[PDB]
Image (cartoon, chains in turn orange, cyan):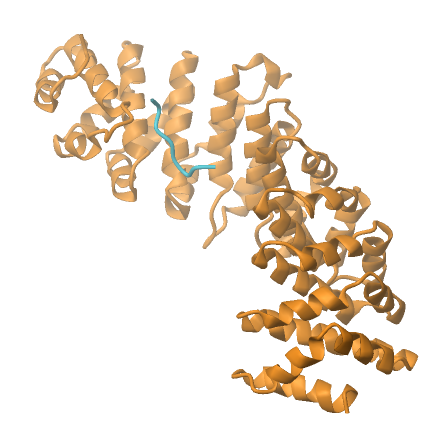
Length: 426
Length: 8
């Protein structure tokens, strides 16, 4: 009977001089803290029990109390930053790192979990866990010929804790820590368990969310083809982080973007740009907008893969955030594209949805659309066809919108719109 | 994924 103990009874048992009474009371605490309904974390903290639990972590001759106190401290560290800090302040970090080497797998796993919660608080505790030396023993647990010999839940918890050591910015994780973790991360990215794949992908997405040097560290390990394969997964919890990572990577240099293209990513975008999950569609369109900001041959590969009609589709009908990203993709396309590429854009039907979006309450999207329209008109000039385009815009009703924009609040807006009128509709 | 999680 360790069920429904009072905190006072727990304190009584833990303050006894009897390791087995302490074990019973720690288990009672664990059971209080592992209920879903409002676990009494703060009451346990106020009772002063964290130091006792931390001391129990070191009791090698009573592994049950190591496990029970590890679980209790895990659940305390799962709370607010103040509660996690309470666990850190009691000395828990080195004690958990020492438990990583336990011969009992359920105890090492519980230490992995606790360290995941501590690191998940934020950059400072993440880096403090690293400074206390957690990475080496964590990776040692994964240094096996075949990850399949490990228990599924254990492997999942190891992957998740590793992902938290890769998470967060200001600052990003230490460069040497990333380099030390990456080979194991790449091995996890090839594992067959959906949750391991998802959390590995999330870690890779964290590591690519930064300057081009971080992106390059990742790309050099050769993960882009595997990311593209996972971009094609049926499980949405895998697609989402794989797509996040791909989008991050194409924020980099034209060469890193080209590595994404060469791996076959564009072939997946017909489905991504029509995906029923709004956030997938939005992130896919954001990624496209960064690809169309690249080189003219990269725009050409966007064309060859049949993706301009899919951008026309998103512009015609999508969540408004997705539509704004699509407008960005079009402006980048027209800013970097050849005359022929811009003409092709017009032939795909861009004008009417582009115009229909000008009645938006968002000023940024209006600016973006007007810039795109100007670039298209410049290509038309280069071809001597500006009247055709003006007639198109007028026939679908866009000229009325542009005229209405003459009396717009923002300076750039009415500057742009009256330039258009005086230059092409006079 | 969550930043933290309790064991229930």
